Amino acid sequence: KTISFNFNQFHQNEEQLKLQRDARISSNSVLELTKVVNGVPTWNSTGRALYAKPVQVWDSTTGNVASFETRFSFSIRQPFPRPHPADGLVFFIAPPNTQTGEGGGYFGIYNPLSPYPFVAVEFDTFRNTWDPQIPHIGIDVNSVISTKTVPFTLDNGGIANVVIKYDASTKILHVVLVFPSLGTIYTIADIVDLKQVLPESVNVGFSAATGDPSGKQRNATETHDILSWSFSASLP
Amino acid sequence: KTISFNFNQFHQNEEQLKLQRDARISSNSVLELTKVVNGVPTWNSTGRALYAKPVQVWDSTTGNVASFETRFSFSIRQPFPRPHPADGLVFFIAPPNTQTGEGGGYFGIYNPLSPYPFVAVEFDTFRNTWDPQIPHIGIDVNSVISTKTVPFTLDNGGIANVVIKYDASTKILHVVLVFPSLGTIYTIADIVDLKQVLPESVNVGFSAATGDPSGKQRNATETHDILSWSFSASLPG
Ligand SMILES: *[C@@H]1O[C@H](CO)[C@@H](O[C@@H]2O[C@H](CO)[C@@H](O)[C@H](O)[C@H]2NC(C)=O)[C@H](O[C@@H]2O[C@@H](C)[C@@H](O)[C@@H](O)[C@@H]2O)[C@H]1NC(C)=O
Ligand SMILES: *[C@@H]1O[C@H](CO)[C@@H](O[C@@H]2O[C@H](CO)[C@@H](O)[C@H](O)[C@H]2NC(C)=O)[C@H](O[C@@H]2O[C@@H](C)[C@@H](O)[C@@H](O)[C@@H]2O)[C@H]1NC(C)=O
Ligand SMILES: *[C@@H]1O[C@H](CO)[C@@H](O[C@@H]2O[C@H](CO)[C@@H](O)[C@H](O)[C@H]2NC(C)=O)[C@H](O[C@@H]2O[C@@H](C)[C@@H](O)[C@@H](O)[C@@H]2O)[C@H]1NC(C)=O
Ligand SMILES: *[C@@H]1O[C@H](CO)[C@@H](O[C@@H]2O[C@H](CO)[C@@H](O)[C@H](O)[C@H]2NC(C)=O)[C@H](O[C@@H]2O[C@@H](C)[C@@H](O)[C@@H](O)[C@@H]2O)[C@H]1NC(C)=O
Ligand SMILES: CC(=O)N[C@H]1[C@@H](O[C@H]2[C@@H](O)[C@@H](CO)O[C@@H](O[C@H]3[C@H](O)[C@@H](O)[C@@H](O)O[C@@H]3CO)[C@@H]2O)O[C@H](CO)[C@H](O)[C@@H]1O
Ligand SMILES: CC(=O)N[C@H]1[C@@H](O[C@H]2[C@@H](O)[C@@H](CO)O[C@@H](O[C@H]3[C@H](O)[C@@H](O)[C@@H](O)O[C@@H]3CO)[C@@H]2O)O[C@H](CO)[C@H](O)[C@@H]1O
Ligand SMILES: [Ca+2]
Ligand SMILES: [Ca+2]
Ligand SMILES: [Mn+2]
Ligand SMILES: [Mn+2]
Image (cartoon, rainbow over all chains, first blue to last red; front, side, top):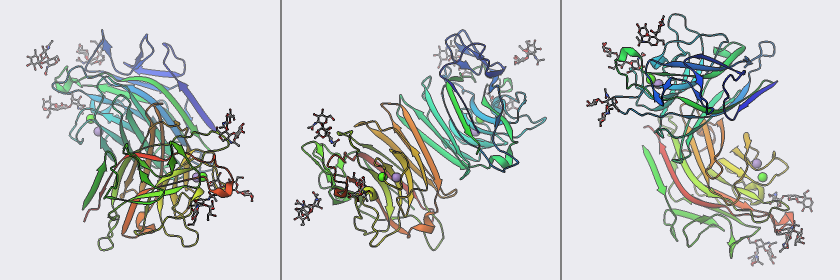
């Protein structure tokens, strides 16, 4: 059982995507997770984008878990250096039919009033009380308090290539971050048992958020654009 | 305890390096693991390069294992597409004071006569009876029959950037291969317990080999050059 999709660019009204909150597809084909007005990113923004169809990560009959690989390119432009950009974007896996969670440092995937399980890879740009120096890549399981973290230097407004790979036989989730214009490479990996934290069917996608009003800073913002995205999963 | 070294280039007669067999440092400073005469790679070649000083990967007293990260760039030029280039290069970890093993598909690290333990990451270009489609990255533990492998497409004569990282806490060995001119990225990882396969002190380095004469093909060859190399390791306590 193999499922896969590829997006070289994005089209307005793409029927295979489910856009939520502020997420929208620009005219020149980029998926803008968070709000940008007249070329300027705004604060108090949150948006998600999910693949329209659910994917099966494991089968309770056979007990088998899927292996998958997804690659995407994103760009984060931070026009206002002072006082601090926020908040970041993530790639996540969650039960189907979920609603956008809290914004800010919760990236829009965590909902305290009614938490749902999730596995996510974050590209965190704002340092909350629970965070190590930013920016950093982090692996999150049911919480934004990462199990593993690695710092990285952002290519402001540049293109970033990401590769996320999960091997069921070893339970290893490894992600690679590359900034071609700088030639830098960042790698992080950890063990995660999907069967143990997620249901048989899930949704995959992205979620991002800009500065929360509580911070009283309109400069706490940046863009969170997704340029392309391909996904592939295999359940034996 | 933290050890590390960085070679942004290679000098003739590198005091910090121990060259074996065909390995040699060119005039323009690249480390040529296998023989190349007048700009042409030859068959029947094998060479290794080890960091002169041994490194401690684990301590029997504390039971602690080290974490490490190594980055290097290499280039493999395949002048003769037919009938098949060979054999590939590897980065390996082995007990100190070992001798070059068999060439060919054994890369010069495996010795059937008297086998010694080793952990290696291979960049295999010839398909032996025990191999999947080539080229591929492979993780080898005491054998060239990889535990895990992933295929990749070579940038002939181009530059390749490699990042190998080992985290003791999870026992995860993850390697990343990138070809900047093509923008391609390959990743592979697996679990390896160093403490369980290697001695407390080891040697780290590279080894490569070209077509073995038994194949009766002088075209079974290619270059195996290392452009730069940095290593780092933290053994807490
Ligand atoms: C942050 O964004 C939210 C969503 O865009 C704002 O809430 C929505 O604001 C609309 C415009 O005023 C209003 O029609 C909607 O009812 C409201 N949604 C609800 C029910 O929460 C949120 O705050 C609102 O908008 C600002 C401009 C003020 O007018 C507030 O009084 C509203 O509640 C935004 N945060 C702020 C206060 O900037
Ligand atoms: C929010 O971003 C603004 C634009 O980046 C900051 O203003 C800019 O501050 C620069 C100083 O580093 C100055 O050269 C620019 O001309 C100015 N641009 C504009 C259009 O405002 C702003 O900084 C605050 O406001 C400015 C006017 C000064 O009073 C600064 O001392 C203030 O810090 C940023 N606000 C914050 C909270 O940092
Ligand atoms: C493959 O490379 C070998 C080097 O590791 C060659 O070994 C030969 O070893 C001899 C013993 O010391 C030495 O005199 C020779 O110079 C050297 N090769 C030559 C001729 O330069 C091996 O050469 C073949 O095998 C040896 C034992 C002799 O019979 C040579 O005449 C053969 O050419 C190389 N094999 C091939 C097929 O080229
Ligand atoms: C070993 O590599 C050689 C160089 O690529 C091959 O020879 C070259 O083959 C080309 C077409 O395949 C031909 O246009 C070139 O002129 C020729 N170059 C030379 C110097 O020979 C060689 O291919 C075969 O063997 C050679 C000797 C010729 O007879 C070719 O016509 C053959 O295809 C490669 N060896 C093999 C067996 O593939
Ligand atoms: C959880 C979350 O969404 N957090 C937001 C938030 O972050 C906090 C920080 O900005 C922090 C730094 O001073 O300030 C907090 O709020 C202030 C508050 O405004 C004051 O009245 C007083 O209570 O002090 C606290 C801090 O101690 C913010 O909640 O905002 C930033 C944007 O600037 C990010 O969006 C975080 O994700
Ligand atoms: C063991 C080793 O290092 N392998 C070399 C070797 O690989 C074999 C293949 O090239 C294979 C292709 O036909 O041929 C083998 O040898 C022949 C032998 O010469 C014949 O007489 C007959 O017995 O069949 C066998 C194989 O069936 C080679 O051992 O050579 C290649 C060079 O192209 C590589 O260097 C491998 O690493
Ligand atoms: Ca954060
Ligand atoms: Ca091989
Ligand atoms: Mn974080
Ligand atoms: Mn192999």
